[PDB]
Structure formats: C-alpha cells, structure tokens
Image 1 (cartoon, rainbow over the protein chains, first blue to last red):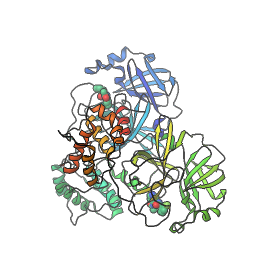
Image 2 (cartoon, rainbow over the protein chains, first blue to last red):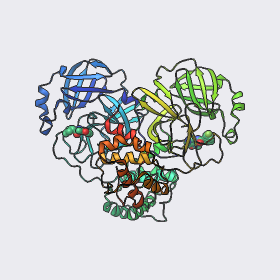
Image 3 (cartoon, chains in turn cyan, orange):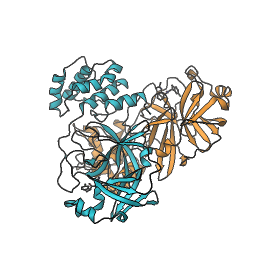
Image 4 (cartoon, each protein chain N blue to C red):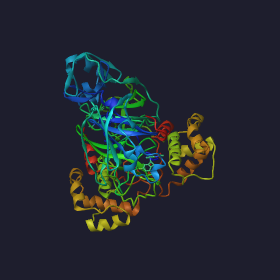
Length: 304
Length: 304
Ligand SMILES: CC(=O)Nc1ccncc1NC(=O)[C@@H]1Cc2ccc(F)cc21
Ligand SMILES: CC(=O)Nc1ccncc1NC(=O)[C@@H]1Cc2ccc(F)cc21
C-alpha cells in the first residue's frame, strides 16, 4: 500500500548523458549510438536569443566547435546537422551504454520521468505530465537544457522530451527527440505565454481509484451522474471533457474496485462543487492529475 | 525555476539490486562487494511471522537454501549470518557494479530516495522522509521488502534504509543497513502502531523559502514572532518545536531571500492559524515537510 509520485529508475538514461559546449554555452546532450542530440540553442549567446537565425548561426560552426564530453573523456565530432530545434552531433564512438530505445512524441495528459542534468551530470529524477497546454511543470535551472523525459517498457527506453526553455511564467517548454516543440513554443527569447492549463480529468479519476485501492474512501458518495452531466461541471472547473475512450481506459480500475466510472465521476463532481472541506486524499489537499490510469495500475501491481 | 519532489538518480543503486529466495519467499537484496544484505524475514513463512524465533529458524537453513540471483545469473552463497534484522549472505563474487558506499543511520526529519524493487528488479524511484515517528510514507507492495533508501554525495551512495514491513495503518517500517529498525518496530506480524506523526517544522520553513525563491510570495506578511511564541503555535498544530540549531541551518536560505527566519515563522504561524484560504504554495494546498534545508539549497543550486 501507499501511493507516491514515482519516477522510472534512471540508470539507463544516466549512461546516455553528455556535456555539450559550443563557445561559451554549456548544456546537456543525449548520446545514443554514434549521435549526440542537444537543443540547437547551444550555438547561441544570450544576445542571439532575441531573434536567432539558427541556419545562419550554424553556418559559422564546424565539427571542432562542438565540444562533447562523456564523463572526463572527449568525444570526436565527425558530423553535425540541425533537425527542427535539435542538433545531432555525429561522433566516432557509439555509446557502449546505449539501451534499447525509441523516440516517441507523447500526447497531452501522458506522464514521463525527467532526469534533470547539469554539465552532463544527473542531479535528480522526478515524474511530470505533459500538460494539456503542452507545458511541463518541472524543476530546471540554467544548465539543465538538454535534460530528457522518458518512459521505460521493461528494457526499452522511450524518449519523449528534451528540455529547452523556461517561459517567463516559470513553466517549462521543450521538444520531442526529433526537435519538434510540444505546443506553439519557439526557441526564442520572446513573449510566449502558456495557454489555459486544464486539469486532466481521466488522470484525476485514476488517482481517485488509487485512493480507494489504498484506503481513502471518504469521498465516495451515494450518487451517480452521466457523461454529459459530469462534463457540464468539468467545463466550469476547467477540467478536460471526459470521453467514452477515457471511461474505457478506466475499465480495469473500475473492475478492480467494483466502482463504476460514472459513480466515481459523481464523487469527483461533488469534490469540485464542495471542495475537500479541509480533508486530504492520498496525503494531498488538492485533486492530483499527474497519474495516468496506466501509472495507477503499474504502481498498484508492481511492474518492474 | 520550479520545485519538485526530486529523487537522486538511481543508477548506482539499480546495479546493486538482487533477488533473494529462501523457500517460498522471494524478496530483494542489496549486493555490495561480496555480501548480499536482505531482511531476515526472508527465512519465514506467513505462519512463522506471528511469533518468529529467527535464531531457531536460521539454524534450519544452510548456505544452499539461499538462492541469490543478479539478473539471470546465480550467485554462489559461501556464508550466512544474521546482524540484528538483516541477513548477510556472503557470495563468492564481488559485485562489479559496487559504487563507493557508506551505511548511515539517518535522523527523523531527514530525507532519502527509495528505489522500489520486486524480484530484484527496480520498478520506481521516489523521495521520502524519515517521519518523526520513525515511519516512512512509501509505496510498497508484496515483494518490495529489501528495497533500499539512500542519498548520494557526488559518487558516494549512503544507504540509510531497507524496507521491511507495512504497518496495519498503511505506513512503512524498516531498518538501517546494520539491521536496526527505525523506531520501536519489530519484524513480527503483531499489533504495532505508529505514534503521533508530527510535522517537520524546519522542513516546512525550508519549503516556504523554496516557494519565495520560486515566485510564490502571497503568504509573506508584515509580522514577526519569537522562537517561544512560534513554538506555542507549533505545539497546538503538532509541529516539531523549532530550535536555534534549526534557525542556524536555515541561515543560507534566509541569506539568499533576505527574509529572517523568525519573519518566515510568523508567516508559517498565520498559515497554521488561518489555513491557505483555497490558495496553493508550490502547487500544493498543504504545508510540505519532506524537503530539508539541504534539499532546497541543492535543488535551487543544481548539485549533481
Ligand atoms: C536562466 C535560467 O535559469 N534559464 C532556464 C531555466 C530553466 N530551463 C531553461 C532555462 N533556459 C532558458 O529558458 C533559455 C533563455 C531562453 C530563451 C529561449 C530558449 F529556447 C531557451 C532559453
Ligand atoms: C502483503 C503486502 O503487500 N505486504 C507488504 C507491503 C508493503 N511492505 C511490506 C509488506 N510486507 C509485510 O508487511 C510483511 C507482513 C509482515 C509482518 C512483519 C514483517 F516484518 C514483515 C511483514
């Protein structure tokens, strides 16, 4: 028993972190096979960030200008190319620690672990969710760019995020491993604002199921609702509209607890309408939305 | 910017996890050099757990009864001994992945990362605190016994916890790596209750400093208080009494923000007396106490 915001073991990803320096800028790179992936803004100075022409800036850079270091050993750069907002540095040595890996672009609402790094060295690991407004609420400082987000499936690491930018509002923006930003963000020091951040309703429900499995049942009421009646309340509280796909995905959690999805929705509706009244659910005084139904099933069944 | 419940990178500890089987019981072991450490209740059946005589039970066990597996390779057991509530299985092969390590017994209020494991395989990593009542609020299922708690200092892993038991109340109990339980708990299936769980005041204050550094300043008021006046309010809310050592430890956070410790105490006092009024601090609707002043300084400065 017990329910915690759990991250995947980071070992396989730690073995891939390198330091990439270009000029005066140092950030993190991801070394997989003979390619080092890093944010393309490594080629910029803070002056360039106002309106960078990355194609023009990259033209003044050669293989020998990109300093790549894995631990205290220097990697030899034999190629460089820009793919969207990431640079791919071809090195002459394949990473001996490359795990089985995939590059996947995640959907808003899905979760992933971040291995926060500085100078190619890991400092910490935490669990995140790709917010519906395509931002992530991470913990990143200067030097953390190039830190990656991933999921693990037994032995296969699915890389889904590379950290690029902190918005003036304190939230974080980045790309998938093909260099495409999540959301409308651009790698430029300009006024960019995150849109409305809605709550991932399906994740809140999955977390309510985790609370029930783990003993917290005070919020269960004698009521039920319909998908349309629940969504009228979800819109008012800036919650994502619940779809039949969401109800289907919650199926195994509903089967395990013996509580129908629409019954759990009625409990959620009353929690939204009346608040927690000073009570907690899984040690939290607010509705948690960063656990997918997959995360709940995984944590409650012990998937290694 | 951003503040997250961060765990240490788990790679160095993953390389130490093994599976220990004795009879029908399978749990996790920690392989360091030529010794595998695991909970001694590995030698018990659920029937023995009611009133186990571990010395008598261990007498019926030989080296060949302890099956140790690191991945899919079997380790040869050449010795076995009981040290308090842990078994130390001497193997003929030193772990090639043994990091620089220490065994340390932590103080209540201090934090550490847990690498939750099943069958010697890691499933997740999360940050915990040793509660003042010597329990931990973890996420552990059947098979998780032997999962360890640790801290990292550059390259040195300090092992501080081994998971042993879940109390009937859903909280967790375990030992240091010498087999001594934290608290009054015994490895027996008997009625054991966790005492009163007080809030780690110094950690709450450090987290208020993290909130200020990271932008959340709504709770800052025009007041101050004294150590004695603050502690009168801390007692009423089951908060640990704040000592001058705690004020001293908060020194660097007070120096960084320019807010005196006793001024932050007055903000905390008003938060205890009036609640959050539906507002949040660092995305939390309750006062967080599982970040030490060291964790805040570490996260906000990027220690790798
Ligand atoms: C100074 C600090 O702590 N900065 C960070 C913190 C957390 N995460 C990232 C950064 N870095 C940036 O946000 C730089 C500035 C800018 C503009 C566009 C862009 F694509 C990347 C960047
Ligand atoms: C069944 C399940 O999930 N159990 C766990 C969950 C989480 N953590 C541990 C366990 N295991 C126990 O608590 C066993 C029972 C007992 C009594 C004393 C003792 F020293 C160890 C144990």
